[PDB]
Length: 86
Length: 133
Image (cartoon, rainbow over all chains, first blue to last red; front, top):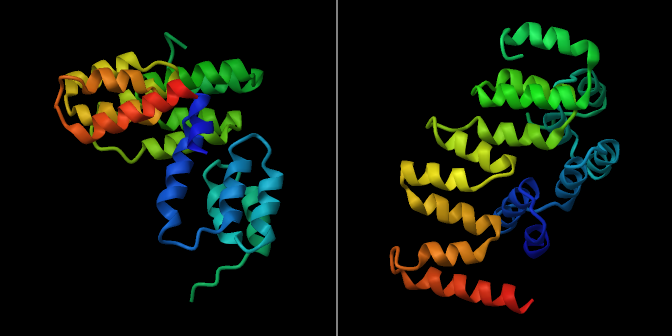
């Protein structure tokens, strides 16, 4: 993955790459979140939303999709997503 | 853009709403060390990667590392190396060069610089792999 992301000049993908390799050893390393981040790194967003909605990552999808300031669709997502914390 | 302020720029550019105009507005906003205008322009342009870039940027302390990371983000690295050099703290430049994937420059920088053996051997092995492939 590093060789492929280095052969062509890319900065965000390689950043996600060292984040993934640092997070692999400790945390559970769920492939759904990283697949969705890879999908959302391009312009196509809806399939990334579907991917995060697939297994269980509603809250992370909400916090991910807030950063780009169109809060209406974030509310649309949070109407279905729950917050199992306390 | 060059004579008037930022808010009326945003107001007069919202009507046209073109990719090139938004891009140039964002470049001007970031060149003046302004992030609110830059993040607004990227949000209007519907670019997620640039928003991730800015989010990574905003957690910085010094006034010069932000400049260097932005300018090496755009397309150009030599001025970033020079600003690292004037700021000193060279291992930052070495890390930037090694993550960018250019190994010959890393080998040239390491030679006669510190004399540490391990990273020189690793860089030479990586450069040999790069030449073999």
